[PDB]
Image (cartoon, helix red, strand yellow):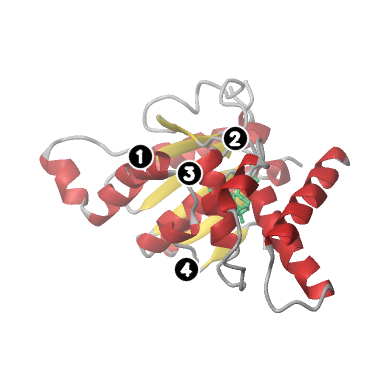
Amino acid sequence: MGFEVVERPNVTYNDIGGLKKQLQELREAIELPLKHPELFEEVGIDPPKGVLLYGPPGCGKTLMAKAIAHEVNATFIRVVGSELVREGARLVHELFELAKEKAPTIIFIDEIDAIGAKEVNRTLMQLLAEMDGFDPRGNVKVIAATNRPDILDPALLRPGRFDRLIEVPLPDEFSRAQILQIHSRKMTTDDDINWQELARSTDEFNGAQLKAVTVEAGMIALRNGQSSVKHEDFVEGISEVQARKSKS
Ligand SMILES: Nc1ncnc2c1ncn2[C@@H]1O[C@H](COP(=O)(O)OP(=O)(O)OP(=O)(O)O)[C@@H](O)[C@H]1O
């Protein structure tokens, strides 16, 4: 095993709420040079080998990464940084070898800070070696995620590495309403549902907690033997997810 391999992920840009601007930057960074690498050679600019997504948990970094891979017909391989801390230089190598074999590939490195906090450590040094190894205009791209871009060893941020940075922030009020709608699409909801009030009531929620709200709302409707989900069900679901946060 070692790291998640997904032959072709079934996630699209329509599954992502809000994030239009940051999704566009990532598409311009990875999708454009994959679909039309010849343009980047004509103009004489090396596209980025690594894109670092940063921001708080559950705001859709992983989503975006899977969605890119889908659009561009690539394999998606995921490693978790905290799992790479024990060996593991060997594992980073096997990762990039496989990724080349199953190319086109999108490598997603979660929690990169676990490995690259600031003659460097042996696992981190493999990541550096592997990225200097493969060339841009090539068809293996790396995407990394972290809370703390400030705590990263500046060696990761040097040219030819993760020299393209995108902030993936908490959803704004409009985004939150989209996120709830998106995760309610498979589920019959009343016409009388006020998505925008629900969005006002979820100040500081992330995408994962908004999805969880949809899930509890659906579960409350079930326990009540309803055949559709009511506004008051979403309001109780918000209240439940807020309770769980408090129970870290
Ligand atoms: N903008 C969004 N639109 C739709 N769903 C979202 C969004 N953000 C988060 N979610 C939901 O929450 C779940 C977790 O999100 P995701 O794993 O992408 O967050 P993250 O930024 O990768 O956090 P981390 O990598 O630190 O765990 C996803 O499965 C997704 O379904």
Q: Nearer the viewer, residue 236 or 31?
A: 236
Q: Is mark 3 within 8 Å of ligand 1?
A: no
Image quarter hosting the N terminus? bottom right
Going from the N terminus, do you reach mark 2 or mark 1 first? 1
Q: Nearer the viewer, residue 112 or 15?
A: 15
Q: Which residue is mark 3?
A: 143
Q: Alpha-carbon neighbours of circle 3 within 10 Å: few (<14), some, or many (≥20)? A: many
**What is the distance, in whole Å, between disc 1 and disc 4 at their CAs?**
22 Å
Badge 1 element: helix
Going from the N terminus, do you reach mark 1 or mark 4 first? 4
Q: Is residue 193 visible?
A: yes
Badge 4 element: loop
Q: Amino acid at mark 4?
A: Arg
The answer to whether marks 3 and 4 mark residues whose Cβ atoms lie closer than 8 Å is: no
Q: Which residue is mark 1?
A: 25
Q: Is mark 2 within 8 Å of ligand 1?
A: yes
Q: Which residue is mark 2?
A: 146
State the image coordinates of residue 180 (x, y, percent, origin top left): 59, 55
The answer to whether residue 225 is above or below residue 80 is below
- Kindly report which numbered mark, 2 or 1, lies closer to the viewer in this rendering: 1
Image point (29%, 53%), residue name: 34
Q: Which residue is mark 4?
A: 8
- Kindly report which numbered mark, 1 or 3, lies closer to the viewer in this rendering: 1
Describe residue 226's horizontal placement relative to residue 64 as left or right: right
State the image coordinates of residue 14 (x, y, percent, origin top left): 43, 60
